[PDB]
Amino acid sequence: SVAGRIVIDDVQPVVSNGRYPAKAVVGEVVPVAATVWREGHDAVAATLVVRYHGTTYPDLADPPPGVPGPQRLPMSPGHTPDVFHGHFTPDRVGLWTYRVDGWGDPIASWRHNVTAKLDAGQGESELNNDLLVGARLLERAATGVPRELREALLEAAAALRAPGDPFTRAGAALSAEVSDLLAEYPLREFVTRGEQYGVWVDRPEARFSSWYEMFPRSTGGWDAEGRPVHGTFATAAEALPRIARMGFDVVYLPPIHPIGKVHRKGRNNSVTAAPGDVGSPWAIGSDEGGHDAVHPQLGTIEDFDEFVASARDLGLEVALDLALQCAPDHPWAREHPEWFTVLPDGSIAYAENPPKKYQDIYPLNFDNDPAGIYQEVLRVVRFWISHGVNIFRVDNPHTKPPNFWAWLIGQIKNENPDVLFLSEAFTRPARLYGLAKLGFTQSYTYFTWRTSKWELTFGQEIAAKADIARPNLFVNTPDILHESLQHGGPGMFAIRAVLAATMGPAWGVYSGYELFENQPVRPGSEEYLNSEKYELRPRDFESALARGESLEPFLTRLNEIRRLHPALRELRTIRFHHLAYSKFDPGTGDTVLVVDMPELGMEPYDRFWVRDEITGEEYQWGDPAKAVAHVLNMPLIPADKRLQLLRRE
Amino acid sequence: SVAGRIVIDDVQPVVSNGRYPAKAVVGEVVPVAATVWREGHDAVAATLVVRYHGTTYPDLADPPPGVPGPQRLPMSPGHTPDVFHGHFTPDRVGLWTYRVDGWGDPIASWRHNVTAKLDAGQGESELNNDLLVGARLLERAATGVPRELREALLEAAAALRAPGDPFTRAGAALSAEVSDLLAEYPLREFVTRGEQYGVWVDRPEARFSSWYEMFPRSTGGWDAEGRPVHGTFATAAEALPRIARMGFDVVYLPPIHPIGKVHRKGRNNSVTAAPGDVGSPWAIGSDEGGHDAVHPQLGTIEDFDEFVASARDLGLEVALDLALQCAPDHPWAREHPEWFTVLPDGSIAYAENPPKKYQDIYPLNFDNDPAGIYQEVLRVVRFWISHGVNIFRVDNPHTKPPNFWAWLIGQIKNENPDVLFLSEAFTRPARLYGLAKLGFTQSYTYFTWRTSKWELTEFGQEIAAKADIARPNLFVNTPDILHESLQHGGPGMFAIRAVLAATMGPAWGVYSGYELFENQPVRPGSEEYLNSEKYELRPRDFESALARGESLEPFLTRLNEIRRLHPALRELRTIRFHHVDNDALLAYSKFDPGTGDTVLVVVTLNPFGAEEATLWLDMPELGMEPYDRFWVRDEITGEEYQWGQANYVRLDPAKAVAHVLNMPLIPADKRLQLLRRE
């Protein structure tokens, strides 16, 4: 939004007036729309300049006191008065930013004038005041294309000058030949420098990703006496072949450092512990270790290393729990008293947030000693990225200053701008949409409570915020046991597993969803029966599968269909017809329909063939015990078309 | 929208990202929104740092190469989560600027839970540390209030420090006494000052104004033979008393300069003229004069100045029409060839804009010689303001590079920012609204094109929404303008269309001839005036029409009276619409922030017979509860009624064509709550 010879107002996308960049993935068509206007009645034109600016990361929030701080592209008019649409697709990861240029254009105003005046029936008599400019028109259009290919200016400018037939004098200048040269090197007149707006372009996984959630402690199993055994790192390097098949490319883990021993929480949501209890993983800090130190019962820091490589050459990506939540036997509760919400006595208050309380933890303080805390925390993350961490699962980020978030995001991404984020928060949209703005790559949504087709109409809200926020559709996580699942039965698994895959290009699953687990601790609760974040929950996938009651063969099918269709990496394409929804593809063209024709690209009457991936049923268009769903390859739309409903306005 | 410990996002109003400032009049309440949030759970609050710096005008557009170039107040939260609502009201003319400040407050977030927890029934046992922060809570703010008045601090901090009963120990810090200690002088902890976006304040006349439009030639009158005779400056100064009463304070006039003699247009829009036809005033430039010259058949310019005085001490304000062109007999058409789009022969092609052809005028060229042009045109206007011309109506600015405008307007308002302009544009909103942004004070709206009960709203829906930028000037009629509606509706639809412009538009207008009811076109279906004064001279006997008791002047003075009587009819954004169960009716209400004044107008779409109806109010915007009865009096007619929310209302257009009544007023706390953007 600037002022000038050409006025360029309302140029999408720009986030919070530019205090942040828009967020994209590489190889994704990104549209930028723009109303622009002028005076009189003469033709107006524009440009979409896109250049790459490396990997250096801009600091988007002002840090606290001690702590530290070209391709010209085209824009085709739409069907909305004075708004324009161009489209760029970034190939490299790193800093990219779009700037819109505005220039009035004459080649086309007289080239139209020629059209109108002779189909209205006029000769050479009336108009030659109008074309003697045309040779003088093409006289500097000449200055704007090379000397060797000047000879081919002179002819038509002469094929305008010398006396000939109305049709003969113009025909030279109308040809594609003459048309070819000014679609490539045009005469740009009266240019207004637009404002240079930004878009940071991440990896794809950052948008098309298959997430999982598993406990490695839980990989312990059963002993000769039939008790649940603790799982260690080695125990877990065996567990992935299973997961790696299903389709996931990134595997998140609950925190993997020592759990404290005091205020520790017992089995079934207890504060009373029993002899040999594991407790809450998210309550970090026993004596023998902290946030960078491993839990003695999963191994050591080196045996950890053997573990992630196992993901390296399987095709999977560890996504660690980065929790800022200490147990009172922490190596900092004594070490650093500073970073706490001290009570005047000398004690630090148990972390509480209503109405769910946690004795077994204490909540950190940056307003106490911001300078001290902040750095340690990166010296912990820096620890991990080296270990081969390219995703960090961030817990309670609305409890932790966004400033802080934005300052770090910088520091890591300034070093390696390849490690990607997920904000797993469910909160006020004014707060909720606020984080990723600051730079959180990905996001958690309130997908859970939203059940109605008129709620899922979620979809309308989500697609519109594709420019910034990126949500992850975890169909399940440890903390809330959604009642639908508990009542819709083994069928309700499929369907909630179907929005999340089809609606969410990046989505998530917690171990056990496959096993149809639906029992809570008590009636009406959405807490899991005998929670794994209070217990070890070894489970037999072989059985359910072998006994032919697993979701495994189907969620690979689901993941198979996802990688099969490039439309399902993308957010903005989503359409909602009459739950039944469609998504189209920009590059390949690929449309799919998951069970409004303009979005289909085909005319209102036509008959067409739709092919099944869930089933395998090809049909000509215009039982939950078998297939509860029905996802189809829709007829494609060609390059030129794909980009036209891609139009932001 | 910036970043920090407190995040202040989506701070309304902001113009093209601030590439233009927001727009205001004096003594007007402006609401300001800003979502702000943070992390975790404890209460946060906010502040609106507001400045006046004077009248220096920011150039909002990058000009061409050669051409030259406090009081801390609060944000009261609303009812949309993390959005807050304050409102500041400017007393001076010139540029003002807004900054949103956000700071966490530990005090009020702390005192809440004592309540929730003492209402959970617990004693001093449980709470006795939680209040041990409380004494060292306000001991900061003790540091944040004066030494003479800590005396009123140390007390309650001690009345909690010494051990006693929780309620008596707590009751102290709760009292209103201290509350004001916290309501005026707070502890802003960890505060972030937002982006200072700006707001320019014109004189009030700039939005609450009554416009009227007359031709000077036509008041010339007749000779012993009774044919239309020419008029001078003095002759018209006689017509103003007439005008002076009706209710206007702003009088725009037709070009008063030498119209050309070549290619010029004759009566009834002819391109064929006769010896001595007056023709187009917008056709400037004969031998005897150009943009600076009065036309000789009106006299000369000294004869122009005592006139503006004649108006200025009747309470009215003269505003010439600023059209930008030349008829081929202009003394520049020969002087300077430059500023025209010469065709290669030595000619310049005639200015038209579709579907209208204009032979007798040609288009200046800013893209030939900008440096050469720019200064004259401004050296043209710099001339007239001296005379006491404080308003200029400017013609079709969608025809002239936007560059010039921001520059034009700049330097003038750098000198004197009391002088106001008006945009006569009917272009696409993307352009029409584009104009007022860079700095054109007011706007023409295609309100005319809007006739339906569903247009009469969606027009409103839009205008009221952008009270921050454009100001429509709702002229009931223009020289070029005369609708099928009024031509068919008879004498009644004059009224009804005259109130669509008058009540909805804080600044609205009227063309002369509207009082005497002329509704007739050149030919059937055409929307131009009959025997146009713009090609012919039209003296008129208003005296006749009123004297015999069918002129509208007495109604548009009644209408102009209530306007000056009720402040609900100055604002753009407060406008609201309650529903009616009659297709041919329509009904809307408007309230006041500063005073509280509410006024409501019910009109019909029938310009003929008695067509009755009933009423559906949204009572909250009315400020009244869904259930209650209120005593309502009619001002044009004079009828009191007690109504509820559902109530019966019949009409008859052969008597009184609409229903406009002052509704019961709204209290400070609420009115500000109803301009509240959310």
Image (cartoon, coloured by chain):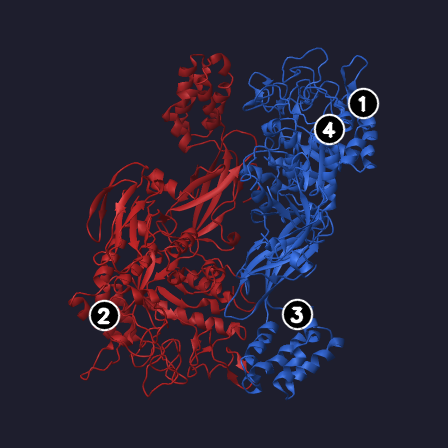
Chain colours: A blue, B red
Give the amino acid type for the residue marked by disc 1 in the picture.
Gly
- Quadrant location of residue A244? top right
Observer-side mark, 4 or 1, equals 4
**Residue at position x 40%, y 67% in the image:** B394
Q: Position of residue B204 (x, y in %)?
A: 34, 55
Mark 1 sits on what residue? Answer: A299
- Give me the C-alpha separation between circle 3 and circle 1: 67 Å
- Chain to which the residue tagged by mark 3 belongs: A
Question: Which mark is drawn over residue B21?
Answer: none
Q: Is residue B62 left or right of residue B226?
A: right
Mark 3 sits on what residue? Answer: A186
Give the amino acid type for the residue marked by disc 4 in the picture.
Glu
Label 3: few (<14), some (14–19) or many (≥20) C-alpha neighbours in 10 Å? some
- Quadrant location of residue B223? bottom left
Q: Are marks 4 and 3 in contact (CB under 8 Å)?
A: no
- Give me the C-alpha separation between circle 2 and circle 4: 96 Å
Mark 2 sits on what residue? Answer: B239
Label 2: few (<14), some (14–19) or many (≥20) C-alpha neighbours in 10 Å? few
- Give me the C-alpha separation between circle 4 and circle 3: 65 Å
- Give me the C-alpha separation between circle 2 and circle 3: 58 Å
Identify the secondary structure beneath mark 1: loop
- Chain to which the residue tagged by mark 4 belongs: A
Give the amino acid type for the residue marked by disc 2 in the picture.
Ala
Discs 2, 3: same chain = no
Mark 4 sits on what residue? Answer: A549
Identify the secondary structure beneath mark 4: loop
Label 1: few (<14), some (14–19) or many (≥20) C-alpha neighbours in 10 Å? some
Disc nearer the start of the sequence (4/3):
3
